Length: 118
Length: 118
Ligand SMILES: [Zn+2]
Ligand SMILES: [Zn+2]
Image 1 (tube, each protein chain N blue to C red):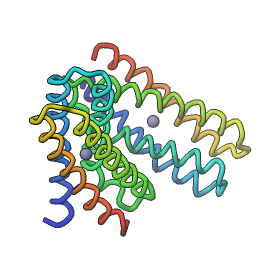
Image 2 (cartoon, rainbow over the protein chains, first blue to last red):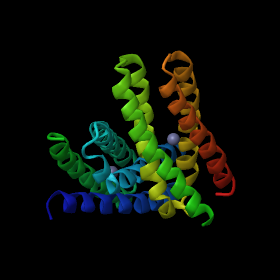
Image 3 (cartoon, rainbow over the protein chains, first blue to last red):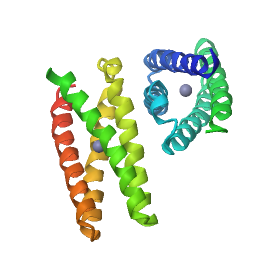
């Protein structure tokens, strides 16, 4: 329970996003979207790695920047995925992007809550 | 043995570097050098996170950029720590930095060997 459970669920979301965004990149085959999604996937991979290891750094000043950067990534992801969602005319994929955005929004709120006190 | 043992030793080196560089920050009390060291520490933390999780991504295109970026960080660390070592007049700390640099050099060689075929 508690925060460790919240972080586990964030990690599970990020893992799913990678798989889902890789499917979306295969369906679309557009070069602007490929560059955006490639970089989002890179971020999501790092978020998984860092949050899996986060206990090691709880007493270390580095924790402030680790969480700040993950939150900043997620904020950028919402903006970019919203842009892609608006640009597309492909209702199934637009709905998938909307659901990913909802996850990213929740992650920002939860990580902000944790970052506040660390 | 094999690559997994090489990666385990790289991770153990990075963990040690963080502790050692944090000691060096505390001995030096020097804001300009300390800012450089704080950024190196942030990189080392991410290297540990990413290499601990690396099996997850071996079949994924992201693996190329994950390893490329770690290697690029290590290359920058050598340049910056070499310049810092030359700047200091503090033989014990200069020797500590020399040994960290040696580790970073070995990491680049081993990760380049691993990167080649992935
Ligand atoms: Zn995310
Ligand atoms: Zn290193």
